[PDB]
Length: 158
Ligand SMILES: O=C(NO)[C@H]1CCCN1S(=O)(=O)CCc1ccccc1
Ligand SMILES: [Ca+2]
Ligand SMILES: [Ca+2]
Ligand SMILES: [Ca+2]
Ligand SMILES: [Zn+2]
Ligand SMILES: [Zn+2]
Image 1 (cartoon, rainbow, N blue to C red):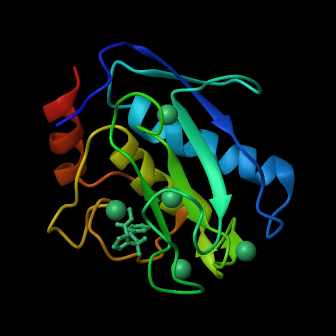
Image 2 (image 1 turned 90 degrees about the vertical axis):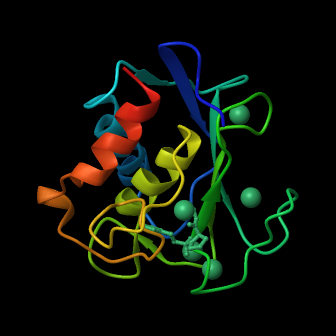
Image 3 (image 1 turned 90 degrees about the horizontal axis):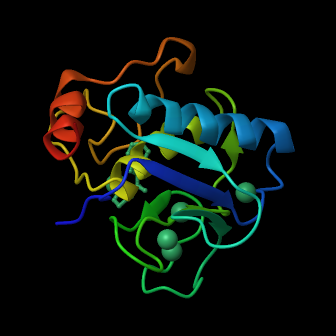
């Protein structure tokens, strides 16, 4: 289904997990948008008020779409594919402990997977792909998209 039909995309952070330093949320989501723009024609800018394309949300339990969070573990996060309104939005379970590192749940790695969803990608059956449906920590410092990921996103864009 959907793909954005424009090159300039905006995101807004709804609120911040108390799990992390503010700046570290900003940076993690920024780095995660850079992953996809590296391999597409898209450009991603953080606006701080009004309607973004992609709204980034921290929330627990019933948070008012249909995709209720399940407490700590299980479903870590979910996102909507492109489209108007809620399309694009990416939602992180505040019942997880979000981190900049190997501990709890790495927000960067998770945000990369969700932005893939915000962008029109589904899951991959490759355990090496960031779009594989099982969260596995890998060094974020040397993180690199799997070739499966690149083919899938370039299947939609560019
Ligand atoms: O895929 C998902 N969300 O987008 C949900 C539905 C089923 C598995 N998960 S998950 O949130 O638990 C983790 C998926 C994931 C994959 C790689 C990196 C982070 C998270
Ligand atoms: Ca959860
Ligand atoms: Ca939206
Ligand atoms: Ca938390
Ligand atoms: Zn949600
Ligand atoms: Zn997913």
